[PDB]
Image (tube, rainbow over all chains, first blue to last red; front, side, top):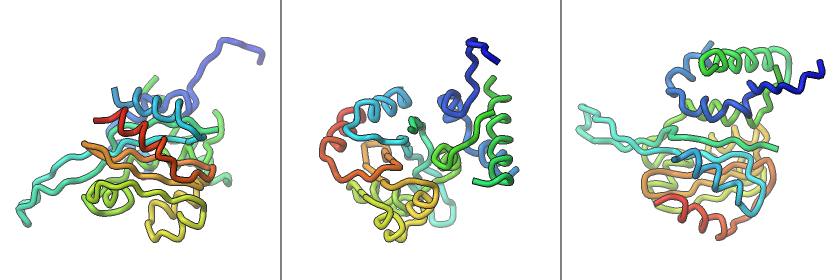
Length: 32
Length: 167
């Protein structure tokens, strides 16, 4: 919608924060 | 810190590496064998980069849940392989990262043949999810792993960089 803005919440953009999350939490989220 | 040096490694790398992972040592005390067993697990990581409905809906859900925690594009197989790798750990000697560490050597699987032909499940899955090259390089406190959707052959220039960026 022609916003520049820009907002980044894509994986590529939050991986740094994701990598710091405790693996056991990633297990549960991935287990659904 | 670690993520910085992981990004450093592939933002200067000779070829195009998709990601880089530091597998980190720890020790858990198994009271049965009395062995302070050494285990490799997720330390940090850096993804750089370049399916079906049931799959992509599953992945998109996970990504927005993490987004909810921290704070809608499709999720490529390499991004997804990178992420699910956070779940994996390796007893010393076991698997591609554990073999590299226990034996203090570099293990270079180049080409889709190498990956599937290795008999390492992590390398096999990697081929499934778009990787063409997998490398594990042992350092002092763990293993640095590089992966790529391209096919890359053993450069000492790489093993050079890794030795520098890590003790």
